[PDB]
Image: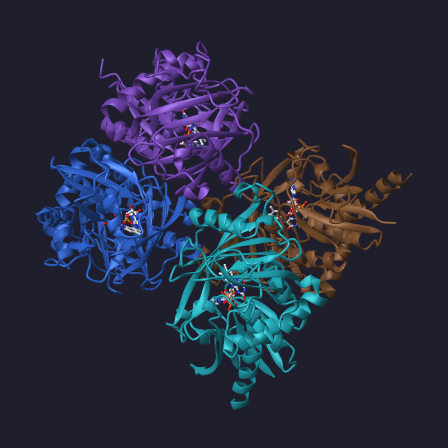
Chain colours: A brown, B cyan, C purple, D blue
Amino acid sequence: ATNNIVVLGAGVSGLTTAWLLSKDPSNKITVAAKHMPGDYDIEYCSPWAGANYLPVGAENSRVGQWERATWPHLRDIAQNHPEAGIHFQDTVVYNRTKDKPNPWYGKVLPNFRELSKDELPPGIDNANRFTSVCINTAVYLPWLVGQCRKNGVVFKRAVFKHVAEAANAHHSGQKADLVVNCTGLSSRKLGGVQDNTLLPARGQIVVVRNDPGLMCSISGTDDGDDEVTYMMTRAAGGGTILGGTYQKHNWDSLPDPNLAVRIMKRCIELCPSLVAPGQGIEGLDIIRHGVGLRPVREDGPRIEKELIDGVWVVHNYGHGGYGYQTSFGCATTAVEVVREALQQQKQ
Amino acid sequence: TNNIVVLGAGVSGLTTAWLLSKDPSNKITVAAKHMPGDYDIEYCSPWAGANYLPVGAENSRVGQWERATWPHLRDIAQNHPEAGIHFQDTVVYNRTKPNPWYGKVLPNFRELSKDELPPGIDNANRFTSVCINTAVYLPWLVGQCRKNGVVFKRAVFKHVAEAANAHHSGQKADLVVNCTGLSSRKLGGVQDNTLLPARGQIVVVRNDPGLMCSISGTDDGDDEVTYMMTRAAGGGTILGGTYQKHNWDSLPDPNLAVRIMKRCIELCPSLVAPGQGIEGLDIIRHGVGLRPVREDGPRIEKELIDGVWVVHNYGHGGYGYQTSFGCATTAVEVVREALQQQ
Amino acid sequence: SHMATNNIVVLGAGVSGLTTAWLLSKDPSNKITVAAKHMPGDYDIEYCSPWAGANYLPVGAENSRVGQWERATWPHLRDIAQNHPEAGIHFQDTVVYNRTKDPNPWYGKVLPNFRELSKDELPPGIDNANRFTSVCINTAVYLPWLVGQCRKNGVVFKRAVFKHVAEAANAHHSGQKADLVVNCTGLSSRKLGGVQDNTLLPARGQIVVVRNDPGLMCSISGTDDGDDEVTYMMTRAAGGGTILGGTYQKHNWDSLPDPNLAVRIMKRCIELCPSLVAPGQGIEGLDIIRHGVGLRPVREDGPRIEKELIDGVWVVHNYGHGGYGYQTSFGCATTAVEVVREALQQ
Amino acid sequence: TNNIVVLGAGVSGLTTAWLLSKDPSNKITVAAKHMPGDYDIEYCSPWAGANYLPVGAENSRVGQWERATWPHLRDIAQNHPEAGIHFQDTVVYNRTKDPNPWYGKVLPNFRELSKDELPPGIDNANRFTSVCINTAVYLPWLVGQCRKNGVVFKRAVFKHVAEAANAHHSGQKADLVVNCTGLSSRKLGGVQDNTLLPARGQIVVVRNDPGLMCSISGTDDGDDEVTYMMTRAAGGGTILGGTYQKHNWDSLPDPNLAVRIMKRCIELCPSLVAPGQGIEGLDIIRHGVGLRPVREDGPRIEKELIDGVWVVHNYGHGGYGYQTSFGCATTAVEVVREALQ
Ligand SMILES: Cc1cc2nc3c(=O)[nH]c(=O)nc-3n(C[C@H](O)[C@H](O)[C@H](O)COP(=O)(O)OP(=O)(O)OC[C@H]3O[C@@H](n4cnc5c(N)ncnc54)[C@H](O)[C@@H]3O)c2cc1C
Ligand SMILES: Cc1cc2nc3c(=O)[nH]c(=O)nc-3n(C[C@H](O)[C@H](O)[C@H](O)COP(=O)(O)OP(=O)(O)OC[C@H]3O[C@@H](n4cnc5c(N)ncnc54)[C@H](O)[C@@H]3O)c2cc1C
Ligand SMILES: Cc1cc2nc3c(=O)[nH]c(=O)nc-3n(C[C@H](O)[C@H](O)[C@H](O)COP(=O)(O)OP(=O)(O)OC[C@H]3O[C@@H](n4cnc5c(N)ncnc54)[C@H](O)[C@@H]3O)c2cc1C
Ligand SMILES: Cc1cc2nc3c(=O)[nH]c(=O)nc-3n(C[C@H](O)[C@H](O)[C@H](O)COP(=O)(O)OP(=O)(O)OC[C@H]3O[C@@H](n4cnc5c(N)ncnc54)[C@H](O)[C@@H]3O)c2cc1C
């Protein structure tokens, strides 16, 4: 007794859901996707990410629980599988006086300490230090492809205009029993879905060779509500990602030079160890610039079943700026919605 | 214990670092300007198809390196699907403008009879070779190095000797292996005047034709070729191509792209649905790399430069993946030789 | 009773901004600064004008505002084509096909050498076809030519970026606060402070620029390749190259040319007017220069030309020209001049 | 009627076409791959600043051409504002870390800076008025001038120079081809000039108007990096430079080089930004890279019978194609006229 599943999409959400589904021997799985790991394109968010684990959800929220559920998997991969491109990094988070002390992730993440009042920079209300992970997305996304392959997942280049078409793309040559929709921001335009609550949150990055040795971030800036500051160093020499930008309803794919300059200035002033004692922006050794669009949904991630044109579909999209840090938690819930959808299909 | 900096993180660098990492007396840093995940004109490896299609003559250095590399690639395609290499049926058509040595090497080798060969075609070979999804394989190689304790660092060097100061131990490296490819033309203390780019333009499509096919030449020009190959694990199909010596142009030419796409659908029509032309190709993107061609082929040899022992492994032209393990095995041999003198 | 002066800032340097600047400059009473983020010679998705074909081929209903602006614009364009070859406009023979899937249009009484194509001559699946002489603008010559025409009349051009329309009033070259600002920011009026026009939307248009000169302009009213895909061609004056189109994708901001869209544009164009290539050739006979994508500044109510007081500054809008900014330019610029003269009456 | 094909539409071709067009016995086709409005690394002209800042020795071919060029540029700036040429105040700083030039006798209000006027680390400095060309207005303006005189323009790619003689708008084989292909003369058939080489120049285009052209003799960032700025006429933007990299063909702007251009420029002339601002004070339009067509012997202006066609070359202008444009064009016309007999 087998189930033909097409996972539509090959970003974090598609790859993590396909991998977890593949652990069930009754699932025969095709990952069908327009863009694959190795691709850089504005329609494909996953490779643009930093990425790190830095919870943004409230303790009792859906997102918060998803973040909480994801950590043990990411820690497991970081501890046991150096081939996956995940490493542990010391992390500092600064919260400005113009604004949260002792967050829930303090009980979860290793080496959590709250910094003393005399250790705080001017303008900072509270700060904390802890161990978390930075994901080298360029190594990790193909690692997930690889893990899916070991469990017999077949990958296939495809483009669909409507979600129900994905059910005709299963490698068996037979109709899929279920389609899992991990199209992210493309679910805004995809037929049978057309989710109007989706919006891009544009994110510009500068990729640099300089290794500061820790992840840094501040709660806000004085450059505007949509210009943020963070940095993280990717595992396995992948480079340092300097950010950033959070521009809702902005679709612009091309790095803006002014914005790039301001990210770099904000970064070298937040964590000066990026550069030598005397230096400004010129001591950064830039690899490239980049821009992705965060698939922000009004109510956050949509993980639910829907019978669409006589095809059972389990959605798993709308992960905004937290798709990696919710990935395993979200994929797990999706695995259960798939089970539930097939259980209704069986009877 | 030997503090080795591998300068470079393309196929040559990664494959050599991996073979070196098998020796526990080696402490290995990979230091490089560009890493897997990067697309840049200075970084050839991501631009490759890539496949195994020998170009060296039987008893040439290149030929023996190609011969030595096959069992490594076969084993990876057989036993490690996570690496992004799979077996593919291959066709090689030879025009007018037979029994090649790889016929005794590659599985399922047959030569085509004249009743099967189209007009203007002299002879053809059919066989099983491999296609490498380089987007998966390059990071896989990073991962295998990582699993063996290899440390990866982002670095830029003006001079080859500087790499000896980038070792992750903090101590001065005993040896630097120069795996900088085409950058060894300008690299301090190497400055190799016999290196030239052979520009290669590609078209990346979603269409899976089920096989690799290539021809010995085209009517579109001396420097224009036809090949296609489908990458493993849904990596896409690579349509080629171009071999343009002393051409450094990083940008895809729209005219060359259309010609690539025209020649490919004519060579192997199963790329497209019956009666479709170029519009039938679902195009992912275009691409351009520069092959690091060297006149005397790959340079693998030891040299004392500014106190630092240097073993070069560069100048692999269009055949860096298909000589990777073979060249890296020679590099290891020369590394042990240079360390014994030390 | 001193020399009467009006300090005007024209905000924007695309066709709307430039044509309106030029018309205002012919009044010696006006002292004019053109302040703009992008200028002729720049390529950017925020700047629609250099992406245009561009031709004259009316889309407005006879008695509609757009239609009347189109009619008013032809004389100016024809005169420039007639008398000023330096401007990069030339006349070209033009054919339009109206398919059976979708007859004596008003421009038949305006444009020279017009004819209805016969019952015998209409190709399969076409209800009506018309041939006529119109104009093709080499935008890469014409936009800088308009800059030059403004400069002759002492218009000062200044690079500037504003978050709010009122800030343009502080950008006048005289050092004094502007009396009026002309808002010609096209699609950027969606986001610009004090304007925030939610009725603006992009209509993405992708082109292929080629070397091949068919010696005529030709379009069709629709295609088999979807509602958002169209077919046209025009050859720019003065060796400017041939523009192959196209695409009309509402609510699509994508700045990058899609290679599949490019191939289909070229396939359709090869079909519609075969003398692009030497017969026996397909797409490979085209000598491609480059690909290009622009976003047409579509407004639901068409072009906004009205006076508004935003903060202390009188503002005259002239934006929302969609895919017809060149063929309405002089018509629209004339109305704005009159609205400016209206607001200055105080 | 002399049927002339001018092969190429950068400064060399356009200026030469315009000069030849003033003789009514010439029927001229400008045939070119790339035309004004295009951006491509095979097309050098739109990547230029451009300004007049002579580099040739007093009695050299180049310096003579620079000298003869000035009055043409001065005149266009004086009487023809529509052409996008700008009079600009100019300062040239010579570092002590790295002399009364001949152009002191050519350019208006030239004066050496006094001892009190020299900044720290500066040996001597020259102040004068020169010209900045808005290449984006001026190139199309030249096309327009050619058009007014009956020059017809044709998009065309040729693999061999002699083929250009078949592209004449009359339909008859051209009496003469003018080779104005710049760096493309290295690969173009019948020419294949191996003394050509690229000198790569990266620029930053900014909105900030400093009010003057600033230039310095050298850098602390290595020989192949330079420092200059110039503001284009008619709101064309300010061009920040730069680099001079022999044999580098690279078309992509390198971000580290860009950052260093911007720092050197705000340090050379701080009125680019406001006091307190660094590189964030610069309002960037875009980055760009062109390849100067450097030739060993400088510009090649001579007749050559290639196949059955008379070819007058005018290429290899390096970083001085604009400031020698008219000088060189005039000589080419003389060479053309002779070749017709
Ligand atoms: C600058 C930036 C930094 C970020 N940093 C972090 C971080 O530090 N931590 C974190 O957790 N998150 C981060 N994110 C967010 C994270 O990148 C996203 O939430 C995540 O990538 C969403 O992945 P996805 O699989 O849902 O969508 P995608 O990555 O967009 O994948 C969608 C898949 O569906 C395919 N597809 C879409 N439509 C079709 C179709 N019609 N037919 C066939 N295939 C289709 C696409 O090709 C693709 O394979 C960041 C995002 C940005 C932009
Ligand atoms: C279109 C195309 C198709 C191809 N197809 C095939 C194929 O089918 N089969 C096949 O076998 N081969 C193929 N090749 C050839 C293959 O890509 C090359 O032979 C191979 O990638 C060269 O590898 P490399 O590691 O030696 O050099 P590279 O891949 O160029 O790596 C060089 C490394 O050195 C680093 N580096 C350089 N300079 C410095 C510096 N100064 N400081 C620090 N680091 C530096 C770079 O950042 C990089 O990490 C193809 C090539 C092209 C262009
Ligand atoms: C592919 C394509 C083909 C077309 N073909 C034709 C055709 O054949 N015929 C025709 O009539 N039309 C055609 N069009 C339409 C035409 O391009 C537009 O209608 C016209 O360009 C709009 O001009 P504009 O000056 O109003 O806007 P723009 O060209 O975008 O000019 C806006 C100006 O405002 C400036 N600006 C904006 N915001 C700010 C700010 N905040 N601060 C400072 N400056 C700012 C911009 O930099 C720019 O200088 C075509 C369009 C496309 C996309
Ligand atoms: C960053 C930078 C700054 C500069 N600043 C200055 C400055 O301040 N002052 C100054 O004087 N100079 C400056 N220069 C130099 C100047 O830009 C060049 O010297 C000049 O533009 C060369 O013009 P050209 O017409 O000879 O060559 P191009 O501009 O390259 O034109 C060559 C023409 O030939 C055509 N062509 C080539 N091959 C073929 C073919 N095979 N078939 C058909 N057509 C062909 C091309 O398409 C083109 O139309 C600068 C250059 C750079 C890169």
Give x and y (percent) for residue B313. 50, 75
Q: Where is residue A213, by image quadrant?
A: bottom right
- Tell me, yes or no, if residue A110 can be seen here: no
Count of marks placed on residues: 0
| Position of the C terminus of chain A by quadrant | top right
Give x and y (percent) for residue A35. 62, 47
On screen, residue A226 versus residue A127, left or right, reads left
Give x and y (percent) for residue B178. 49, 74
Farthest residue to the bottom: give it.
Answer: B341
Look at the picture and state if B153 lies above or below C278. Answer: below
Q: Where is residue C41, by image quadrant?
A: top left
On screen, residue D148 versus residue B320, left or right, reads left
Look at the picture and state if B118 lies above or below D40. Answer: below
Give x and y (percent) for residue A176. 78, 43
Look at the picture and state if C93 lies above or below B330. Answer: above
Along the line of sight, the residue nearer the viewer: D310 or D222: D310
Along the line of sight, the residue nearer the viewer: B311 or A56: B311
Along the line of sight, the residue nearer the viewer: B193 or D211: B193
Along the line of sight, the residue nearer the viewer: C48 or C10: C48
On screen, residue B94 versus residue C21, left or right, reads right
- Tell me, yes or no, if residue D239 can be seen here: yes
Farthest residue to the right: give it.
Answer: A347
